[PDB]
Amino acid sequence: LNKSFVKKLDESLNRKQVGSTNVTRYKIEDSYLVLAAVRVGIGGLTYHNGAAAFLEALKFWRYGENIYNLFFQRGAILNAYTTLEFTDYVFLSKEESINENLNLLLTFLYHHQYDEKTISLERNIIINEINGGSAESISRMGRKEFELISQKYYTPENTSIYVIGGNQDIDLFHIPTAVMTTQYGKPTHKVNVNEVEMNKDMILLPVEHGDYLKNRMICHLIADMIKHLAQQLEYDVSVGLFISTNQHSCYLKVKKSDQKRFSSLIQQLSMDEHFIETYIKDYQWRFMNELVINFNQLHNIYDYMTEYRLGEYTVAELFGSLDSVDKLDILAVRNELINQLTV
Amino acid sequence: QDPMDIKINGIKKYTIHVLAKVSASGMEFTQEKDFEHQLLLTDMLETVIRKSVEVNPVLHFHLRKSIIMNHSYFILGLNYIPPAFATKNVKSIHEIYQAIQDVNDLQLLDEFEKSKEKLINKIQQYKHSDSHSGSIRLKDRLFADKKYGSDRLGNFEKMNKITDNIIYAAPDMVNKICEGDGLFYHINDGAIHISNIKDFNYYIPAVINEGVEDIRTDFSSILTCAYTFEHVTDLEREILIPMFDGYIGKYGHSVLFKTLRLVDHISSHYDQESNLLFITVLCSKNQLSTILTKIQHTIESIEFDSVSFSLSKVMFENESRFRFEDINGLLSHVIKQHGEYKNPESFLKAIQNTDIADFYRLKANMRWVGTSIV
């Protein structure tokens, strides 16, 4: 809305290549901590169900050393987690420790040797974690598979780095691990959404109408509209979202048991002519307000960088995309949703 | 005009500005006999006022009756886009007061049942929280007054039987919120502004029923132990004891996790309101008597060391920094802390200046007082 605020945010936001990876930087003056996030794309591993999570556990180990313990002794808590397309390694610390903590983290992530006893130990842990074919698939993979997968996916080229808060720049001199490359380039963005993400009792509905950013806008808009209409009719419809950084399209998750009710609500959207227009206006106002509020928490800024690729895109482009969503975009996606629901 | 403008420099620059008023009450909250009524009307008021005030540039409106060290306060807050980035200026405090006084009684009645159900749910969830249930029972018996434990969020029986003629007490609440004396806090442009210096004196209930065992019978186990500290200073209640709780409770290989791993779901928490350190753990009845004696002996013979103490100082500083990251955590900190601790930099510097000799004073002043088992 107000141009000087969008301009204010964008002058703190930047993204540049560092070595063979990329660093997205959002500087915050006088922030109390700095958030660093290292994100590895593992979408291709979804055909080996559970391999990405297994790798995540292996990556905490290097020459008998555990990087969670090393970080803990330095007063930093390292958190990691694996979604369908990425494995994240995230930590908070004071800015003075960012360079050394980040380079130590990349030292572990770009280590590619794991002996037999380490692999079998992490497998045993994951099997007990299953009880507390995901368990089956990692039982069919050995040392040579995990080491090859590490060399193919845990590379600078397949890594995104995000550093939020503070005011120092990340450069190659301080992070020489950002050139620790292998003979393998960035892998294809293929993904086994069809098995891991959905099971046979759900359906995926594509929200894809051209624009990467607008797909997120329209997907949230339609999910919010359907939830509100379900509230008024007191439906029981659960609408999940599949919104992933490496996916150009966005997707809605609806139980196969709720398909008829969901289909009725999608058709209900165009019943009131002014409902779509005024709901778009409300969403645009709520989106900007929430961004203003959310840009005070480091983790929330990180979520904008992963969902909307903020850094590659500017905040001005984010709001320009938001302001370009119209009634015709909603109707076009409504029509395509109905065609998918029909067949 | 304010009597003062206490500007605390070097603050994190947030995207929003904050304007808050904190209104005191010299009565410890057990003395208030209309406690459940004041809670319900306050939530009803917040909901109605929010619908009128939460428009541009205001992003969030806050109005709560909060308890700070066993004294109740009305806390009104306003988050808004600063005028340099706003297409409309923010209402003055006088205009905010006027919106509160313009609240319609029918708007309040439309929220009565919804607010009453919201507060009823908060009391039941609070009393029924499995891990939190043990500590509630101890505070009731240790202090011989269920307002410190079970009825801290309001007595259920009193709250459940409130009718909608509570609407006639709305003028008294509006007057107390608007005309009651208080301190103003203003966050802008990398600084916090306070309108005056008044360190509202804390109150901590004295223990009466020392040494409590709470036997319970119910199948599918839980254990909760409580300790208190004598001669608690501001440094201890705000920094040292929270550090000590983290030392023995959650900082990785805490003393209890290492001690109880020998037997082979542990939690500990220092309640600053009641000056009590709780320790709860899930276990089996066959592990019950052993873990009780094991926990007690470990606390009794506890020792420290400067390397691990330096780590607790680093950890607790970073936890404080994470709270300062949030504009509400910063505001809450500046409201509650006394004197120079109000400045986050001074509070962090005070953490860095603690020494291990402080932990040995705290160990000598430590004493067991309670136990609950299910």
Image (cartoon, coloured by chain):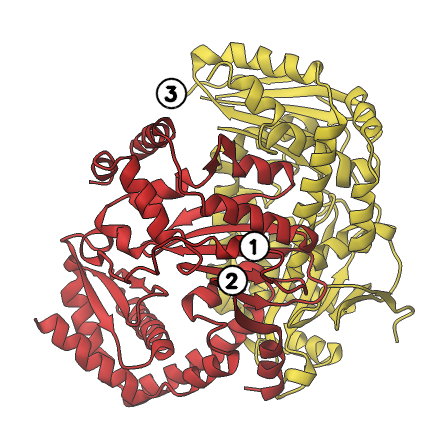
User: Which chain does yellow denote in the image?
Assistant: B
Determine whether A144 is above or below B335 in the image.
Answer: above
**Mark earlier in primary sequence (1, 2):** 2
* Closer to the eye: label 2 or 3: 2
The residue identified by callout 3 is B219
Res. B150 in view: no
Determine whether B282 is above or below B81 in the image.
Answer: above
In the rendered view, does B93 fall on the left or right side of A253?
right
Q: Chain of mark 2?
A: A
Q: Amino acid at mark 2?
A: Gly
Residue B97, quarter of picture? bottom right
Residue A266, quarter of picture? bottom left
In the rendered view, does A127 fall on the left or right side of B238?
left
> Which residue, as the protein is rendered here, is positioned at the far front?
A183
The residue identified by callout 1 is A176
**Residues under labels 2 and 3: Cα distance?**
60 Å
In the rendered view, does B71 fall on the left or right side of A212?
right
Q: Secondary structure at mark 1?
A: helix
**Residues under labels 1 and 2: Cα distance?**
8 Å
In this view, the residue in front, B138 or A35, is: A35
Residue B332, position as x, y percentages in the image:
70, 55
Label 3 packing within 10 angstroms: few (<14), some (14-19), many (20+)? few
> Which residue, as the protein is rendered here, is positioned at the far right?
B3
Report whether mark 1 lies on the same chain as mark 3: no
Q: Amino acid at mark 1?
A: Pro
Give residue A19's mark. Answer: 2
| Colour applied to chain A | red
